Image 1 (tube, rainbow, N blue to C red):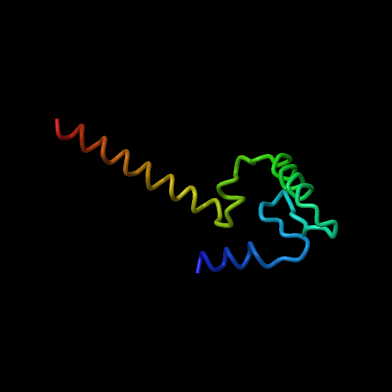
Image 2 (image 1 turned 60 degrees about the vertical axis):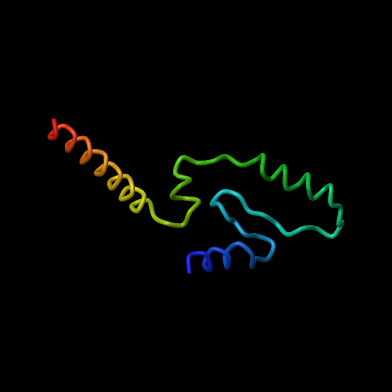
Length: 88
């Protein structure tokens, strides 16, 4: 369902998608120039700036889940070091 809700978001779209919150991708034009379209897609990749909260902003999951992931891995590290000190 995660892959389904993502693919339903990335393909269906009419002239504007806005996959990342900053950039919108328009549909290809009538001129049918493939080199011009290649240059347009490369220019659209060059203009972008990766935000700091990209892990929570570009991916639609909330940032509290990110904080939960950091808390769990921090807990695993703190527990293993505490266990190693207690063993010696």
